[PDB]
Amino acid sequence: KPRIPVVWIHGLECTCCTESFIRSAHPLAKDVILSLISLDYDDTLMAAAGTQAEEVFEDIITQYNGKYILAVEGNPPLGEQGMFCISSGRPFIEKLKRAAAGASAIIAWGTCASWGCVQAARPNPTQATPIDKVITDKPIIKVPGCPPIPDVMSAIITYMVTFDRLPDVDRMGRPLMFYGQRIHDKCYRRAHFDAGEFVQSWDDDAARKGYCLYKMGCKGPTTYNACSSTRWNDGVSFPIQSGHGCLGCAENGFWDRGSFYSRVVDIP
Amino acid sequence: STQYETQGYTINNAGRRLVVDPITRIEGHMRCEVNINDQNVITNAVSCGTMFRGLEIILQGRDPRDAWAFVERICGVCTGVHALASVYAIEDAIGIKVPDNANIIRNIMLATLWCHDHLVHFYQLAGMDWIDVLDALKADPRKTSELAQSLSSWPKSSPGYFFDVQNRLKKFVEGGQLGIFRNGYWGHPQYKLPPEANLMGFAHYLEALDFQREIVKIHAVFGGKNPHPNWIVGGMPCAINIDESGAVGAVNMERLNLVQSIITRTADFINNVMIPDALAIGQFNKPWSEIGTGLSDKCVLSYGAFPDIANDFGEKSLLMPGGAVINGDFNNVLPVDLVDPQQVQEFVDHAWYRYPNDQVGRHPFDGITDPWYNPGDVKGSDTNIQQLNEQERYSWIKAPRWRGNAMEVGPLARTLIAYHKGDAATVESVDRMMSALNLPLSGIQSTLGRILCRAHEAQWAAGKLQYFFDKLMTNLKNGNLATASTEKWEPATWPTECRGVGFTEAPRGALGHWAAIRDGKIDLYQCVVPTTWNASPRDPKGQIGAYEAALMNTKMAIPEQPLEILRTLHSFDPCLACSTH
Ligand code: SF4
Ligand code: FCO
Ligand code: F3S
Ligand SMILES: [Cl-]
Ligand SMILES: [Li+]
Ligand SMILES: [Mg+2]
Ligand code: 3NI
């Protein structure tokens, strides 16, 4: 049967979200593209360039007006009349608005599209602005993280295809399924936290026994994501498991919450 | 229209103007414009970076220990390479030496990135410039099997397999939902592979899209996650415990077994799928050994990479050679110094930035990142560029030069530098590769050569992964487990004022981060990134960068279908987020 049309556009970004997507272990990104959705526009993978790429974009948003999902990676800069990000000679924000107008719903992949991420960190030279501050008349599902977990991305996709509905979301638009709990709520080092067993400096005896990273600045206690349960790259690891505290990368403004190595101030 | 001469080229903007915006199958945002003459030959090429985020500005005032995490987000494709450059730079400034295992693990991280980034580029980015996917539908599955088996011992080659792949493509296309294949250049006269080779290549495109996900498991073990693994100033955070209580909480024998399993599989795939495919592309596209030469026979640059002696960044330590060649003089590989203010300089007279004097170049320790969107007289308006004005400012990319010379960086550059320094392994490999194609050495200096060198490098990196893993295991056997130095972790131990340079060879070429620390905070942080070199706009002398030079003099079969432009640009693996940062 026909597959759901998907248009994937890119603003200011580093492309980590697109890269995370192709890391998916199940379903493989190959199988998502071949069998689950129709990825009809995507600057990073598509054969067409320049005018041919413009023709694809125009044809798809026209033919499937009201019926395609818009995936967004990165964000629009408002500075310099939007010309910090230029697409087909015009501000990226114009392409974003045109694509959003015909979409049935929008997926804001990553902390960039959800919140701002690194380009929005102080002093935000380009006035990088998350999607939901520009597009105010469309369902937007925020899937934050820098990048989000590969198998979370593909699970969210399969949920929408299989159940023919958007996932239920929290008050911030994040899917409850993966963002309902804190990293710290499902962290395998929590026994050490509770016992006051902490890494105090890198590669100390505590580090070699996998003690808690709280005193090394772990932001797990204030961060909502699936890293400590679903884990990363086919369940191989996550930041804390490999010895570094959570940076807080799924949370709005995480870059400007003080040093990554400063302790969480008020643990909820 | 105007005409001028530079670097042996005649830059002429008379004639039809062609615009390609967006450039697709790259990372980030790029616009290209060319002029073509009455013979459809490119007489002018204009490289434009169409994005900027300003990491150099954002980094000011940050804790130097945090810098790697910020600058890692320059790019998620070459993920980790900016973190490595950052920790090197901060360690250089402060005066930190890391333990041997930390250095070995960092080398593993970089070699893992090379394998991953090169493999995915070859198939997912550049592949469709060479393989006509739609033409795969006309292939005979038995003849495809016979072709594959003539090229490689790779197991996956049955007629039934190629028939299954072809059938899946048939069903994918049949409903009219062509997705990433829609409105492509299929049928272009420059597609020269027979149908069996197109089916073989398409099968391998799918195999690579599946397999690349496994390579980065090495980053997950040592760095927590990929994309964007974690690092520390002073070493790595992945503490090791092999034979003591609590090894479940650290890098242990099971974690190392996983790493070894990935290394073996990665080498297998690169050696038996990517390498034969690259050579096959070479065999069927030999005229491309004479197209897209650009600066590769004039000026090439490598900083060098993979220090094998921990904390030693000298010629005797770096496993990947550094050096510069200028003026086509490959008999004299020149030493590079990243502190010398007369060597690396960046110009902005053709870029969207303010300098007090835009006619002079600034070494990164004197760098300025003051964005200034000022396109001047485009055809169009400030928010509707119909034609960039390459006589004034036309890019978010700064113009790096080395001793005032425009340089090419990347796999071909590195290969030429190693070859001409007399690296025995490189000479043997290059000579054997060109012999197999019955091409002269000069054939490497081309668009086809960039692709061949990239494949060569993926093979080299996969071999080095085992070398570094064995080095790590040797230390562990000798009871050397240290992964972090923390003597100078605390800001109270740092010089009040210091500066440092971190450098490496990222997949796309020479990378440097220049950092100045004052009173415990980043005072200045300037990046010059490989695609900054290659995608460079012009300088005050009108000298053109690697992309513009490689596009010069190129015949196009069908002006409105920019396949030759895409082939040459994609051969450099452009990363525009890197170039602009
Ligand atoms: S502070 Fe971090 S390492 Fe410690 S239990 Fe919480 S999430 Fe885990
Ligand atoms: N490779 C790579 Fe990215 C670029 N250019 C960096 O550094
Ligand atoms: S840094 Fe990000 S990847 Fe997960 S563990 Fe923390 S939310
Ligand atoms: Cl943010
Ligand atoms: Li002009
Ligand atoms: Mg820079
Ligand atoms: Ni990059």
Image: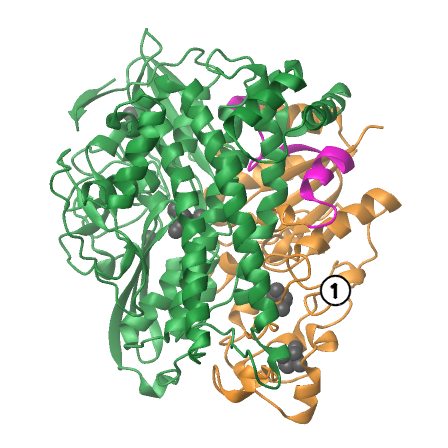
Q: SS at mark 1?
A: helix
How far across and down, in percent of the image, does residue B580 sit? Answer: 39, 47
Mark 1 lies on residue: A179
Residue B448 visible from this viewpoint = yes
Relative to B185, is A2 above or below? below
**Going 71% across and 54% down the picture, which residue do you hit?**
A151
Q: Which residues are magenta?
A: A25-52
**Going 68% across and 64% down the picture, which residue do you hit?**
A231
* Residue A51 among magenta residues: yes
Quadrant of the image where one finds ligand 5 = top left
Residue B326 falls left or right of residue B17: left
Q: Quadrant of residue A39?
A: top right
Farthest right residue in view = A163
Chain A hue? orange
Chain B hue? green
* Residue B492 among magenta residues: no
